[PDB]
Image 1: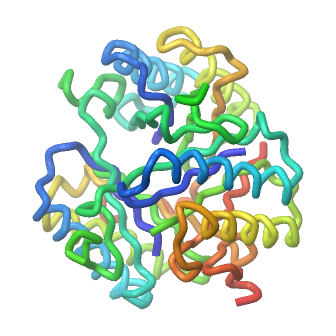
Image 2: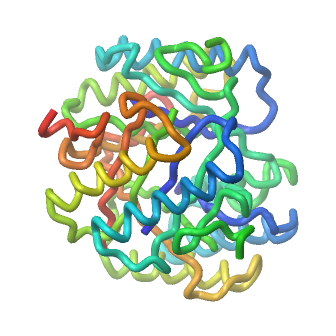
Length: 116
Length: 121
Length: 108
């Protein structure tokens, strides 16, 4: 239900809105979550502040953090890690090897929707 | 004690400084933490880069991650839940139901403050 | 493998590349990870947007998130805590008092 992507600053509006759609599209399908319950945001990392193996991109990648509450088994995570990863290689493209998808489970005692 | 609020790019300097005080005040009251211990950062997301349910805000939310050390019981989490939620629906307001709050407990073996962990203090 | 440092928007290119290198080098040594598997990014927070005990920096600091896969034992974490504390005082410099490191275990 919360997906943050850290990516390099090259991408255009269009790639952004299709990347949002896709992560959202890829999320509702795999884990069967509500579309209106899906939040995404992307984060432009400047080439001057993003390093692969110790040196900046400017001197020379896509990271996806998923925030679910814990109601998901390992198989439905395999599918999510799979679906999140595939559709981001489709639009706002990048090799599969260069996309990392992270799953952070939040205890229901630790996620607050409105007051509760 | 580590509070990142992800918000849209509208908010003025006043709203920011008031949002920072409010989340800090909310934290110290809720979890009885030292004010000196409370670091709060706001993350301004362009509308073109924030999606609600598949489409961007520009084509058409408040997300608060807290990284604390693990001591807090259920009730002091729920209060941290409501207190951060209320104070932010107060200043630089948005609807209650449009603010989401994430509580991440990092183990004492995994939190490093100065050179030392909290475990070896 | 994933190191996000949040910092104020004051630092030069040189401080930045030396920070990326110092975080990568402190990483590869301690936890013996592959340089090419070490990604590190810096997130500039403007002063109006970074608050300590309730006031904005401007009205008047480093937080380092490490996300590895979950095998790491206590000592390699405390060493990780220390390697990435120290080499961030060497360059993009700051008093140790004002740096927190955060270790996030992630492993399906």
